[PDB]
Amino acid sequence: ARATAGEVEGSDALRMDADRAEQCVDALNADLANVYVLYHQLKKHHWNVEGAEFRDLHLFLGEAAETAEEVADELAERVQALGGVPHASPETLQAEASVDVEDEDVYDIRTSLANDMAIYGDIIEATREHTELAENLGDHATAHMLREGLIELEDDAHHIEHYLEDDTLVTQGAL
Amino acid sequence: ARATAGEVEGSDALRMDADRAEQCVDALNADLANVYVLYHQLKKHHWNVEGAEFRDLHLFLGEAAETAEEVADELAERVQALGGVPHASPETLQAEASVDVEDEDVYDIRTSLANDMAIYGDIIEATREHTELAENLGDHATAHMLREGLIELEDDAHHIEHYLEDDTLVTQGAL
Amino acid sequence: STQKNARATAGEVEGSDALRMDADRAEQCVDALNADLANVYVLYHQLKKHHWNVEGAEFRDLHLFLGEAAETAEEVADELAERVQALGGVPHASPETLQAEASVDVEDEDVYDIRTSLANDMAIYGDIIEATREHTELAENLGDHATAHMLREGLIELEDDAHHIEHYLEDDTLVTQGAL
Amino acid sequence: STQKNARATAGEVEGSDALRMDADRAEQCVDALNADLANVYVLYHQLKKHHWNVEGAEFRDLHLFLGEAAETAEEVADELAERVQALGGVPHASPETLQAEASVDVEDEDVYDIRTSLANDMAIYGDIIEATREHTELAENLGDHATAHMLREGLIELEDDAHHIEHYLEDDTLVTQGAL
Amino acid sequence: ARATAGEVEGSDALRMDADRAEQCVDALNADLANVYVLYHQLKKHHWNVEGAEFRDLHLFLGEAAETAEEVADELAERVQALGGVPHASPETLQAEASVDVEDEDVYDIRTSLANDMAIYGDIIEATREHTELAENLGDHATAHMLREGLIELEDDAHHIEHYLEDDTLVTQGAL
Amino acid sequence: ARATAGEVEGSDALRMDADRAEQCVDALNADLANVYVLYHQLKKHHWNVEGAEFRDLHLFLGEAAETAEEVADELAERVQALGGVPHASPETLQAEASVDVEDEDVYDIRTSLANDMAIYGDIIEATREHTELAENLGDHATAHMLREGLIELEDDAHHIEHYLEDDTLVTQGAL
Amino acid sequence: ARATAGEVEGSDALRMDADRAEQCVDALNADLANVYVLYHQLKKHHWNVEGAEFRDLHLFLGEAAETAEEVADELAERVQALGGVPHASPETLQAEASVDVEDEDVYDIRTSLANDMAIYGDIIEATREHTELAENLGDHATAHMLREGLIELEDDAHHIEHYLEDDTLVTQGAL
Amino acid sequence: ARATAGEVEGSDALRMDADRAEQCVDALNADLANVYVLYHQLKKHHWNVEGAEFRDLHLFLGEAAETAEEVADELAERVQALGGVPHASPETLQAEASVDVEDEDVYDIRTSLANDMAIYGDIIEATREHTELAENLGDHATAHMLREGLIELEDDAHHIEHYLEDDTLVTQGAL
Amino acid sequence: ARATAGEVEGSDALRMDADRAEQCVDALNADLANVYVLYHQLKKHHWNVEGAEFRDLHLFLGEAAETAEEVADELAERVQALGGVPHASPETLQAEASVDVEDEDVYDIRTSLANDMAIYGDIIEATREHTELAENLGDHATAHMLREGLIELEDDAHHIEHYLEDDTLVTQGAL
Amino acid sequence: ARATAGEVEGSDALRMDADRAEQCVDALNADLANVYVLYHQLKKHHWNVEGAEFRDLHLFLGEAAETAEEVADELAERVQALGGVPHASPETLQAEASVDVEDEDVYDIRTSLANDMAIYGDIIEATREHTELAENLGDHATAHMLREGLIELEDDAHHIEHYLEDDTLVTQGAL
Amino acid sequence: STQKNARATAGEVEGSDALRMDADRAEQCVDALNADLANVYVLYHQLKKHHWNVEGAEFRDLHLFLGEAAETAEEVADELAERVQALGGVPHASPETLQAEASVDVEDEDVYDIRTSLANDMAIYGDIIEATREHTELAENLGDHATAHMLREGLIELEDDAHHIEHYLEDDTLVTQGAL
Ligand SMILES: [Fe+3]
Ligand SMILES: [Fe+3]
Ligand SMILES: [Fe+3]
Ligand SMILES: [Fe+3]
Ligand SMILES: [Fe+3]
Ligand SMILES: [Fe+3]
Ligand SMILES: [Fe+3]
Ligand SMILES: [Fe+3]
Ligand SMILES: [Fe+3]
Ligand SMILES: [Fe+3]
Ligand SMILES: [Fe+3]
Ligand SMILES: [Fe+3]
Ligand SMILES: [Fe+3]
Ligand SMILES: [Fe+3]
Ligand SMILES: [Fe+3]
Ligand SMILES: [Fe+3]
Ligand SMILES: [Fe+3]
Ligand SMILES: [Fe+3]
Ligand SMILES: [Fe+3]
Ligand SMILES: [Fe+3]
Ligand SMILES: [Fe+3]
Ligand SMILES: [Fe+3]
Ligand SMILES: [Fe+3]
Ligand SMILES: [Fe+3]
Ligand SMILES: [Fe+3]
Ligand SMILES: [Fe+3]
Ligand SMILES: [Fe+3]
Ligand SMILES: [Fe+3]
Ligand SMILES: [Fe+3]
Ligand SMILES: [Fe+3]
Ligand SMILES: [Fe+3]
Ligand SMILES: [Fe+3]
Ligand SMILES: [Fe+3]
Ligand SMILES: [Fe+3]
Ligand SMILES: [Fe+3]
Ligand SMILES: [Fe+3]
Ligand SMILES: [Fe+3]
Ligand SMILES: [Fe+3]
Ligand SMILES: [Fe+3]
Ligand SMILES: [Fe+3]
Ligand SMILES: [Fe+3]
Ligand SMILES: [Fe+3]
Ligand SMILES: [Fe+3]
Ligand SMILES: [Fe+3]
Ligand SMILES: [Fe+3]
Ligand SMILES: [Fe+3]
Ligand SMILES: [Fe+3]
Ligand SMILES: [Fe+3]
Ligand SMILES: [Fe+3]
Ligand SMILES: [Fe+3]
Ligand SMILES: [Fe+3]
Ligand SMILES: [Fe+3]
Ligand SMILES: [Fe+3]
Ligand SMILES: [Fe+3]
Ligand SMILES: [Fe+3]
Ligand SMILES: [Fe+3]
Ligand SMILES: [Fe+3]
Ligand SMILES: [Fe+3]
Ligand SMILES: [Fe+3]
Ligand SMILES: [Fe+3]
Ligand SMILES: [Fe+3]
Ligand SMILES: [Fe+3]
Ligand SMILES: [Fe+3]
Ligand SMILES: [Fe+3]
Ligand SMILES: [Fe+3]
Ligand SMILES: [Fe+3]
Ligand SMILES: [Fe+3]
Ligand SMILES: [Fe+3]
Ligand SMILES: [Fe+3]
Ligand SMILES: [Fe+3]
Ligand SMILES: [Fe+3]
Ligand SMILES: [Fe+3]
Ligand SMILES: [Fe+3]
Ligand SMILES: [Fe+3]
Ligand SMILES: [Fe+3]
Ligand SMILES: [Fe+3]
Ligand SMILES: [Fe+3]
Ligand SMILES: [Fe+3]
Ligand SMILES: [Fe+3]
Ligand SMILES: [Fe+3]
Ligand code: NA
Ligand code: NA
Ligand code: NA
Ligand code: NA
């Protein structure tokens, strides 16, 4: 084995001793697993959303899933750069995720979206925490990447919140 | 006149005798008719869609019309390449169409969409039969082009079906 | 006079020698275009407002529509301002001035539902379209065909937005009581 | 029944009236495509894993290859999932489900050397290719030529990746004992 | 009314209670109004700049105005995401702006630019302050967006400073 | 010879008899001449501009030449479409031009620019009259194309006028 | 030597045993040779076409060469992937082709294009059988590629048939 | 006046003394004049070409004009850079050209293209000598530019020779 | 002299008094010199890398050098914006660099890369330090730019680390 | 036959008599042969490269084949423009080639590469002689095109030479 | 010898067998190109310097011009370095080496006004152009037409920059005492 899950060696290139590195890696791994379940649930909703607004949502959800995917990729790579091993198999990603994930049934779009927003909220707070963690270890690259992915995660979280708001152009009339 | 409607001459270039070619031509030209009436009816719905979801549907139906148009173009070009005469005038297209065609009035969006979905379904079933028929004649290029257009037609048809499904983000609350 | 600090005084129109447009004709266009610039920039700010705030089942489509509609208004206002300058006048500039010179009705700072918001934008669009229609004839009658042509170029875009908001507000939807 | 909260139950296939595919035929494809989706999404996660972790003399070329190969798998899985939905079934979704429904062999969480990792991806690719080959005939025999065509479109890409990993693993190199 | 100017509800999606949110929203709103007057004064100068260097300045000022516009947009959207109401009408934006705004006369380019730079300076210091505010509330997305717009605002502020410096290629000779 | 300079034949395709067409042709061909001499003189100024602002003016005059060239192209094509013979040789272009044309020496930038501005102004006034003349003949396409070229010519002319205005960032200080 | 011409080892990666693989290979290589001489012949005709319609044909022939080149590449790369040795040197490619190839003199453009046409037809018929062969061996990726290359070949052969058709805008008049 | 036609001051920047510079200038200007009348003649032919092959020739002639235009620009800009005055007005350009220019009547397309061809050949031979001249003066940048312009001129002259070649897809049959 | 090396005047535009500014400028200048030696050593290795993996490394090293170049540019510009003078001549950049730089011999790729990674490590730690410096002076733009360049510098540092890891696809077998 | 292989007619358009043209033609056609066999052999190596570095080499050899192909195209077009007949069939290309051509077996990568490098070297030396020969005939366009292709051929040849050099990131450690 | 650690020694030229250029001819080009690389890289650093620092009425146009002019020099130096390597020599690399091997005059670390700065760049450009002119003949006389052609490709760009700086410095301007 080149590396053992859970081993964190830091990096001589990046002058981050294993001690500091393992504190970021533990936090980014936790992020990774959550963000990857988020991606797979966004994919799910993307695939399955139906009804009057489905095309727009479909497009939104596919974009959102692309954005979680990229954030996952940046996390896992950071992990590795810090001498860690990013969670990889689907089983591992779900087991190490703390966020709640829907069972295999398909739910209606409102429920589906409120479940996604719950996920985002938990990721967003965790992420805020890890960025202060990274800055306090002086890992400013990690903190900068966490904030760069945060602002995209909150923009999708906020979109979803707007989808779920109590307004519409529909009227009883048109019904 | 350089060629007479209905005639099929095959093609020496393509090493397709008129007797095989007539078989695919008669099938392709009937596809052409139905696709071009589909194209016109999508155009109609694109122009006329109104209401809470209209911009999205407007784009979608635009794109589906462009897809229909390109399919029709490929079918007509293929008919010509096999030495046949592709149906051309709008009056002939509609007259050769087997699918149902709305009258000039403008129906509401769910009615229009369900009318389009029924046209898609007839086109999809005929296309499936035509691809078999082309493979059986060893006209693999034809069969191929039919599959390549089929998967586009099926994706549009499936999107319409999603639009019509019984889900929505709208709640009585928001109404 | 040689000694104002101001390069130009608000309200002065000086025509252009480059453009062979004397001050007399210029003033007639610049009066029209300034008044439009003011309305189109309040339109732009209200569309932004509605882009920012729209929520609910159709929000993302509206959010993008309304941002594109603000962009178009922005571009229209930029043309009209540049035209007023090219004609030797002073385009309305500060936000206060722009709203004060606008004749359209502007929402107060509360956020309303999307149908109310769209209806209010619709109303501004219409005012601007009737006015732009007038100003184009005005400009053609002055022989200022550049300005006329520009007014029509921007009119076609404003009417396209206005008409989209009209469709958004129409009584139809895919939604059924069933799926409710 | 009118009263499940679930819009759809995992494992139900309902065909599509749009697509003129009754539930009987649909179920046969959706069974095949679901099983593929599961394998292709575990493939995708393992390629990502190997993209993340590859190191050594050839790492940057492999890192880019393996990221492009994950992207392709991702796109393949997205097609297959969308197809399963279009056919009125429920594509496997959660990571746990996807791995549980995968028949391919997946590496444990340790990181292995690049030859071991590539070999393991190679093995998944092959399984997926033999299966996809079957499913394409399956689909053509059902007259579901759209699905068949899509399976072939994605098969050509998967085979191209599989074959590249084969070349990466071949016994040749520019490296000489000399330069060692 | 869906929302009242001045109301700040936080966001459940973004796990930001109204208490913390109202401290960012108050600061971003203040920013918004200033940045929107800045945009309208940049537009003004863009439109009106004349003389030997006017084309370059025109281009620079239009770019600068585009950049303030985008920053405004990111601010107002953040505000909304935080459950606030971003200042919207032109009247409101100018009244809530703290920066000084030129009267409707047109001034020469040097004066015009020195007035713009004053604006930028006030926005830049405010923005620095709000970013420490956001980080201290642990709103790291807001802080990250503030810094992302800061660095573009200081780059334009600095350009303007260079335009106004005491150098030129011109010589008495050439005059 | 396929056609003789001066002749105008109208066009059957365009349903424009030679008697209406001659009227627009004589106007368009006089525009063509003046625009092509404008184009050459902009080229000249583009090649020769020197001094503190030269790169900017160099680009500008380049672009304005390209605009002039495209206008000339549209005018000449239109003349041809109306069955006329567009003036072609450089000697004929200049000879048919009514505008003033610098001699071969190179003047300073303000002189050159003011010479161009005077050419623009003559072209703008003639274009305005030609558009009226075309609308009055019911040649709306012509009138349209003239308006579309006019607004470009007017914007270049206005830019030159801005260049010549009595403002600058330069101060005696910096000198 | 790493591999010997004519040997075909299949592929473990693609789960194609040597037996099935030798079948597709022997067909794909014989295509490869024909398609590469086609490529060189189109290049020839591309280089040499002269006369009234030369620039158009020059562009079409260059494109048709490029299409043949890419078909050749896909063929050869498939052969390799199946564990075979694609024919490589020019003399091997012409020796293994079954199509007729013009001698090194240059023929007028009708004769040249008629000869290409003969070449396309032969390739097209071969490709059709090979697609059937690959499908029958269950080598779907190979069949799918041959169909993809086929529709481009057929499009080309068909364009050449149109070039050669007995119509023209020319009239005696214009002679 | 800033510079006087015919004067050539060299360049200190380019370390080209007036003597060497006057040599390249006198050659480049005489190219400039010829290439600009070439440009206007191609424009003419572009505008006027009619008949069976007109759209293709129209596109080729427009491109060939654009190529000549850019060659002219590079020539004139080099002259300027060498401290000379590039010929500018249309009447100067035709007066200083040594090529033959068609009168203002419109000739059929063979005659028109034969005349262009005469013009290209003369320019091509001149350019060849000038490249030799520049190299001999050690003015490598000038020679390198002339070669770069030359290969594009030659490509054009050669296309015209192909247009005029005695072949065609037309047959009596089709007449 | 407009400015003296080492003088730092702050900026009125950016409301950064010279006192605070000189603390960032001193730190960014140190960064600049190091990052510019890094760029010149990356260029070196880019140019000279040979052997089995050279093309990929070449591409990687040229990209890395482009990224250091951009970071240098952002540093030097910040310096200037803060009223400082960025180190400019090559001599000055090397003298003020603290990182070790290879002599003019060419070393093998492994050695070359391990020398580069040493450089990156020193720059990365310095950069982390300066970002906390900038944040503590409330220069949040500087801190934001430092982090934006940090994350690219650590990504290259980490790549290099991966190149140097003890894995390969090579086997004794293949040797 | 429109032209007979070997004949060279020069060109009137290009003012190149057959006696000068034959000299460049005989040289260009021998280049063409060797370049097209180079192209085929690069194709071969592209298809067949395997092992630790294969993807990179695969791309490289692909690109170098495309470069070879474009060089061959330019050489053949030039031969045609000078009134010669470019060698066309694959059998003639190889037969006219003076370079060595692998037999059909597939060699290992270092052997293949060194075989290509030897073909490059013969082509580079001949090209150098041909450029001299073209300049001496005053065929500057030819000489130019040869230099423009030479520097591409030399860069590919130099890249192959880099691939073959005795360095690597691989260590016995990693083995 | 088998045992230097250095792969190549600075100053050694070994020709290339790939390029069929023996060491004797190569050395003559590599001497010329190295000397140019050094000057062009000091040019690049001084243009950067002036891009960074230019201020005043025309600064943004100059800032962009001078950044594009540095980019071109950078690209020129990269060609020349790669060429020196391709010819089996060792391109000057460290900043110290590059300036030490440069024959051009380089500004001290103070910032001068834009006319002084431009004049100083102009002076470097000229040196480089006269030298490049020589080296191109040198290379053609050696029959190294690739190098000659590359020298001319980069010469045309350097002369275009040099000539632009010449225009920037010319005695003309739109500015009048009036507007002063
Ligand atoms: Fe769907
Ligand atoms: Fe994605
Ligand atoms: Fe990645
Ligand atoms: Fe990584
Ligand atoms: Fe690692
Ligand atoms: Fe970013
Ligand atoms: Fe970004
Ligand atoms: Fe609420
Ligand atoms: Fe509509
Ligand atoms: Fe369409
Ligand atoms: Fe279309
Ligand atoms: Fe078509
Ligand atoms: Fe036909
Ligand atoms: Fe056809
Ligand atoms: Fe396709
Ligand atoms: Fe249902
Ligand atoms: Fe905008
Ligand atoms: Fe915009
Ligand atoms: Fe503007
Ligand atoms: Fe003005
Ligand atoms: Fe328009
Ligand atoms: Fe228009
Ligand atoms: Fe109604
Ligand atoms: Fe993706
Ligand atoms: Fe993707
Ligand atoms: Fe999708
Ligand atoms: Fe569904
Ligand atoms: Fe495809
Ligand atoms: Fe396809
Ligand atoms: Fe202006
Ligand atoms: Fe903007
Ligand atoms: Fe926005
Ligand atoms: Fe928002
Ligand atoms: Fe909200
Ligand atoms: Fe950013
Ligand atoms: Fe960023
Ligand atoms: Fe960014
Ligand atoms: Fe100062
Ligand atoms: Fe110039
Ligand atoms: Fe032009
Ligand atoms: Fe042009
Ligand atoms: Fe034209
Ligand atoms: Fe005509
Ligand atoms: Fe026409
Ligand atoms: Fe237009
Ligand atoms: Fe004044
Ligand atoms: Fe082997
Ligand atoms: Fe090609
Ligand atoms: Fe290939
Ligand atoms: Fe292989
Ligand atoms: Fe395809
Ligand atoms: Fe016929
Ligand atoms: Fe002077
Ligand atoms: Fe042009
Ligand atoms: Fe130019
Ligand atoms: Fe000059
Ligand atoms: Fe070029
Ligand atoms: Fe002949
Ligand atoms: Fe190299
Ligand atoms: Fe770079
Ligand atoms: Fe910069
Ligand atoms: Fe700066
Ligand atoms: Fe400064
Ligand atoms: Fe960024
Ligand atoms: Fe970015
Ligand atoms: Fe290790
Ligand atoms: Fe291969
Ligand atoms: Fe190619
Ligand atoms: Fe190609
Ligand atoms: Fe070609
Ligand atoms: Fe010929
Ligand atoms: Fe030719
Ligand atoms: Fe080139
Ligand atoms: Fe060695
Ligand atoms: Fe660069
Ligand atoms: Fe670059
Ligand atoms: Fe490079
Ligand atoms: Fe080397
Ligand atoms: Fe070039
Ligand atoms: Fe070139
Ligand atoms: Na809705
Ligand atoms: Na100035
Ligand atoms: Na013809
Ligand atoms: Na290797």
Image (cartoon, coloured by chain):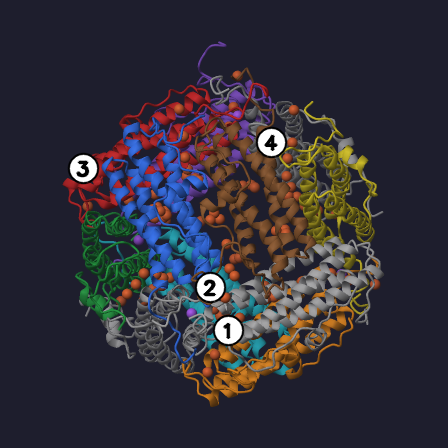
Chain colours: A green, B cyan, C purple, E red, G orange, H yellow, I blue, K brown
Q: What's the CA distance linking mark 2 and mark 4?
A: 43 Å
The type of residue carrying mark 4 is His
Within the image, what quadrant is residue K119 found in? top right
Q: What's the CA distance linking mark 4 and mark 3?
A: 55 Å
Query: Which SS class for mark 1?
Result: helix
Q: Do labels 2 and 3 share a chain?
A: no
Within the image, what quadrant is residue I135 found in? top left
Confirm or reject: label 4 Cβ below 8 Å from ligand 56: yes
Q: What's the CA distance linking mark 3 and mark 1?
A: 61 Å
Confirm or reject: label 2 Cβ below 8 Å from ligand 59: yes
Give residue A106's position: percent from left, percent from top: 24, 66
Q: What's the CA distance linking mark 1 and mark 2?
A: 46 Å
Q: Mark 1 lies on which chain?
A: B
Query: Which SS class for mark 2?
Result: helix
Query: Which SS class for mark 4?
Result: helix
> Does residue G86 appear to the left or right of K49 in the view shown?
right
Residue topped by disc 4: K167
Tell us which disc is closer to us: 3 or 1: 3
**Residue E23 marker:** 3
Mark 3 burial class by Cα count in 10 Å: few <14, some 14-19, many 20+: some
Q: Which of E94 and B161 is in front in this view?
A: E94
Task: Look at the picture and state if G9 lies above or below E131.
Answer: below
The type of residue carrying mark 3 is Gln
**Residue I54 marker:** 2
